[PDB]
Length: 339
Image (cartoon, rainbow, N blue to C red):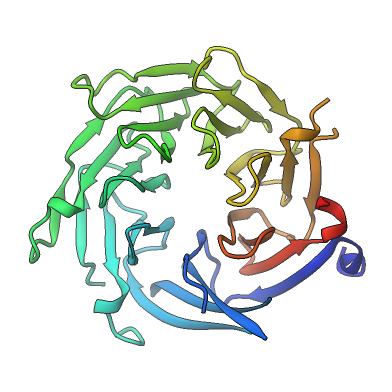
């Protein structure tokens, strides 16, 4: 694979980190080259990490913040990207404003968020209501907090609402991109559930489909279409969904030869979606080419399970993917391949 790269990439960078990261997300600020930044974590003292990346038109660690337990997931708040929520290996979800913490570390989170009885990974900030955070847990619950309602000197926040519709481990949660009340969740009970926070019944979802034939592990809403979202599963399938007819699956993307953990739409291209998991492959899909023609690219760079990945928001087709052997890769498939 390493020998074949000039054929398949316009860019590939490999970085062995000192510790594995379970988490990867590009921050939205970019400053011959340009400087981009990634939110990462450690697994096995733990830190919340901000790294720098030079990209054309080196990777340095900029910020390490003491974290209790590994960082299961870390997500920046869209309305103030200095704010980062993290999932811990305990019931706690933590919140850090990276500017209120030392350059190098000495765990003293800015907020500790209560309401779960077990650890999880799923985590999602509302991009339409500032400080509304959702978290999914192995306890079968989804918790909601409004951190914007928390007093200046408040360090502890109880869950505003707990959603209980699921009957198994809740794997992932994600807000809708346009509708401030609407989010989706996926769980081990094989369901996708669409929830409406304006509803008083926190035990029953607005809609509910039996999405998959095994555990549903991830979901992602389309940033270009109000109606479209995708799920990924222990099914080894990515399923496609329309909010106007949830009961029938629009499509199935086959396939990974193993369990799917992440699915994310492109921020630049409405027909483009990527997925990954335990087969150590990150696949890029093209809706438009359905009628496997919809498989546009297989990224074979990783030699361990891929933990998370993120589409760079400033630089089309750039992806950061991180694996369980400590490897972070920043890569862009060849222009020849998408156009």
